[PDB]
Length: 157
Image (cartoon, rainbow, N blue to C red; front, top):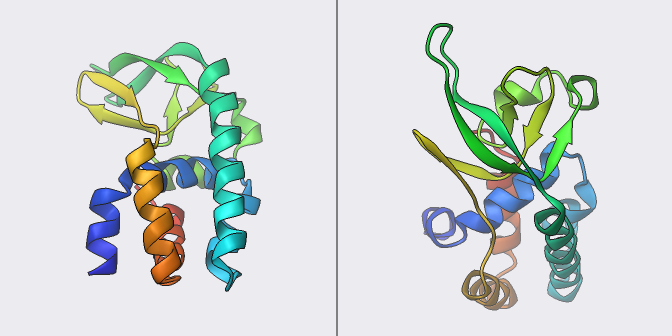
């Protein structure tokens, strides 16, 4: 069950790669789909993980809308890895990647960040060593893990 177990165990990687999809940094996605070389895929992921620390280290906090009601919008403090102007993000993306793009309260700008909502609170999700280790190992035994990971990341929320 390469897909269901990937969605359970490597959920934090899926969420990271989706963050990059939203930013259209497809250099970190394309090799997982088209490359037949595990070494090349591991290289790209190492670069992806490193650039991700630049984001997680530089982040600012904003009050974001985690549940959008016309009357009682639920807002939460969340770390925003990127704060984007509305016209810097594709028009269709906010409704596709709904748990990666968030409205910043009392503002037109977007919070772009791999967050998970537990309706009240928002939590930054980052891949831990275990997940990276495991995925790299699975990847060496079967390249399909790259294909399915990218497929899920590109998918909406």
